[PDB]
Structure formats: C-alpha cells, structure tokens
Image 1 (cartoon, rainbow, N blue to C red):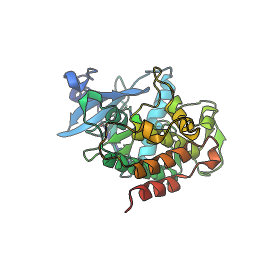
Image 2: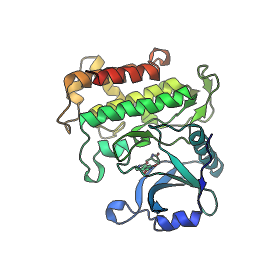
Image 3: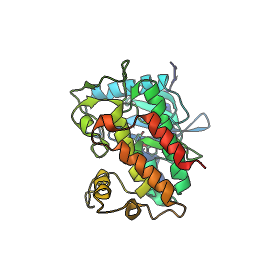
Image 4: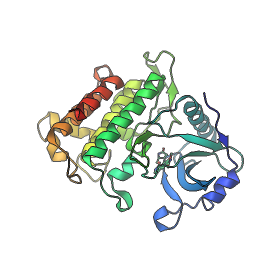
Length: 299
Ligand SMILES: COc1cc2c(OC[C@@H]3CCC(=O)N3)nccc2cc1C(N)=O
C-alpha cells in the first residue's frame, strides 16, 4: 500500500518536448505505444523517466480509460517487485492522464526480439534470464491475488541489465478467492495471446499462464505472436504443427542467436507447450512454470 508522486501535466509536457510523437531515432521523444496510450522519454529531477500519456487509440470511452488509470495506480501501490516495472508518479491535472515510470533503457521484449531500430539480437543466455524474470514477476502477481489479463512481449520491459519488468496493469483484476473462476461482460486483452476461456469472458490466473506460453514461443523463435502474411498467422498454432510431427522446434528456433543449445531450448519449449494446453485445468500453475524454468538453466 504505497502513495506516489503527483506531477503537473505541464512539467511532463515540458520534459517530453511537448509530447513529441516522433520516434527517438529521428529526434523525437516517442519510445513506444499501446492500445491505450503513447510512451515518451522524459527528464525529470535529472532522472530519466518514461511518461505514458493515455489516449483512446482503440474504441474505448473516457470513463473506461480513467478506470484503467486508477486500476494501474491501485495495483502498483500494492505490488512492488524486482520483476514489475516501478511507477514513480502520475498526472491527473490538465489535458491528459499521464503515468510516470522508472526508465527502461532497453524498451520492450517485443522490440528487442524484432531488433527494432537496429538493436543487436538477444542471446539465448539473455532470453533465459528474461523468461525466468518474467515468470518471477507473474508469480509475485498471482501470490498477491492479481490476474494481469494482458501478458505479452510488449508488456515485458527490459532495464539497464536486461532484467524483465512486467508492465501495464490497467486491466489487472484482484480476487480474494484466487481460485473460483468468474465471468465478465467486457472481454479485454490481446487476441493473439489470449487463452480460449479468456476469449469467452472467463477471468482466471490460468489465462495468464497461457499468454506466458505464447511469450515463451516468441522468445524461442523471435517471431511475433501474429503475422497476417505468415503461415501460420498465429504463433500459437506452431505447437500443433510440432505435436502432429509436421515440424520440430529446431525448424522454428531464432537463427539470430549463436549460443542456443538443443537441451535448454527443448526444456523452454516443453514449458511453453504445457502453458498452451487448451484446457485451463491441465496447464501448470506459475510456481510449476518458475521451477521448470530454473531447472532449464541448472547445472
Ligand atoms: C511503461 O513504460 C515503458 C513502456 C514502453 C513500451 O511500451 C509498449 C506498451 C505500452 C505500455 C506498456 O506497458 N507496453 N515500449 C517501449 C518502451 C517502453 C519503455 C517504458 C519505460 N518504463 O521506459
């Protein structure tokens, strides 16, 4: 139960060069974006920070956007951990709602897997630490009775040491009876990562495990979760191709690595495969996932 800094909108507007939407690669301040806002690089109190300015980028109301702003703050006040991005403050005065975070110099796992802007590919050694760190962050959330509901590589940020930091808690849901699955009338999340039961309205921590399985496939292959000009379009379908012996995990391993070994790659794939079980009750819990990922690098 934390209390955060309250920033003025105009200081955040000033330190981000009037919310310069041009990418940093061309002299702007934009680091990235989501369906609910744009992230800008800022400089407050000599400290580099990230400023997420909330906007209706997809079909969403002002009231729903304010609820996600409040929910992010509420979750960040309760959940502080090594593998969760740190909220420094917020801005609720003036024109837009802003959320200020600790600066993540290596951006998102999605951007690093795609080598966006010419960044060097992540080694298998770094990818293993990222998978372990992301699982430790999800474990902390589930231990504190929170369901993220939007686990994906755009929501796994990378700090100055490539430590994984789960981000975007605007859709997170608390549950005193952590088990006991409930339903919602507003289905939210990212389609390419969503569990079948989440697509139907169910709210359960088992859906976070399924989404994490898609993230593990992106880590192994370097492929995005969805690509409309690829066969298969959805990355999750490669699990079925491998099960039906049409292909092997070796046919899909990211070629942009030089230090992957068959044993640890097959160990990570086995975890991803278990996470992606269509029946939610057959998936492992996050504790089991954490254990399997630790055994993957043990020697
Ligand atoms: C929340 O803080 C950041 C979000 C970044 C980002 O986000 C893409 C989506 C939208 C919001 C989200 O959480 N994921 N892409 C690239 C770089 C980012 C850096 C930070 C940062 N803290 O430096």
